[PDB]
Image (cartoon, coloured by chain):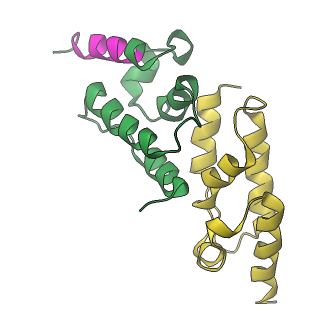
Chain colours: A green, B yellow
C-alpha cells in the first residue's frame, strides 16, 4: 500500500489550485485524511492541517478561529465563490 | 501560536543537503512542541517528519524500524559516521 508518512507528504503537497473550488479541495484533502489511521486526528486537527493549504482568498476571508467544522468551512468558502461570479 | 501555521512550517522545513540529523530533528521538535500538549503521540510526530528527511536517511533507515526519535537519531548518527 502507502504508509502514513507518505500520506502526510501528500496532504501537505496538495495545495488548493488557483482555479480549484473549495468543494473540490476539501474533497481531495478529506480523502487523503481518511487514508490515515482511524481515530488519530479530530476535526480540529484535520482543519489545522489544511487551513493553510487553502488559497489566499479563503484564508483572508475566513479566519481559522471562526470555523470549527468542515461544514462551517465549506459554507463560507462557497459564500466566497458566489460573490465574485 | 496558531496550530495551522506550525504545521505549514513543519512541512515547509525539509532537511537540507548535508544537514545532519541532530540539526533537523532539533528544528522539528521545536515546532512539534509548539502544538497543543497531548495532541500527537511520538509515533505520529515521526510520521510527520520522516518523509522530510534526505534520501540517505530514508534509504538506510526504514520508518517501520524506528519507534522513537532517539532510535532515529542513533541510526542517523550511524549514517553520518559511515562517511566520517
Q: Residue at x 69, y 48 (%)?
A: B45
Q: Residue furthest left?
A: A85
Q: Residue at x 49, y 45 (%)?
A: A36
Q: Let me know if residue A77 is in the magenta part.
A: yes
Q: Position of residue B29 (x, y in %)?
A: 78, 48
Q: Let me know if residue B38 is in the magenta part.
A: no
Q: Position of residue B80 (x, y in %)?
A: 77, 81
Give A69 or A67, whichever is nearer the viewer. A69
Give A15 or B17, whichever is nearer the viewer. A15
Quadrant location of the N terminus of chain B?
top right
Q: Is residue A77 above or below residue B48?
A: above
Q: Position of residue B18 (x, y in %)?
A: 69, 75
How many numbered marks, from 0 up? Answer: 0
Q: Quadrant of residue B8?
A: top right
**In the image, which residues are magenta?**
A73-83
Relative side of A55 to A66, left or right: left
Amino acid at each position: 500500500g502507502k504508509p502514513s508518512y507518505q500520506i502526510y507528504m501528500e496532504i501537505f503537497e496538495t495545495k488548493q489550485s488557483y482555479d480549484e473550488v473549495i468543494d473540490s479541495f476539501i474533497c481531495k484533502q478529506r480523502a487523503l485524511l481518511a487514508k490515515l489511521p482511524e481515530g488519530r486526528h479530530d476535526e480540529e486537527t484535520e482543519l489545522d492541517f489544511i487551513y493553510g493549504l487553502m488559497q489566499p482568498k479563503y484564508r483572508e476571508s475566513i479566519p481559522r478561529h471562526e470555523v470549527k467544522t468542515f461544514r462551517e468551512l465549506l459554507d463560507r468558502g462557497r459564500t466566497v465563490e458566489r460573490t465574485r461570479h
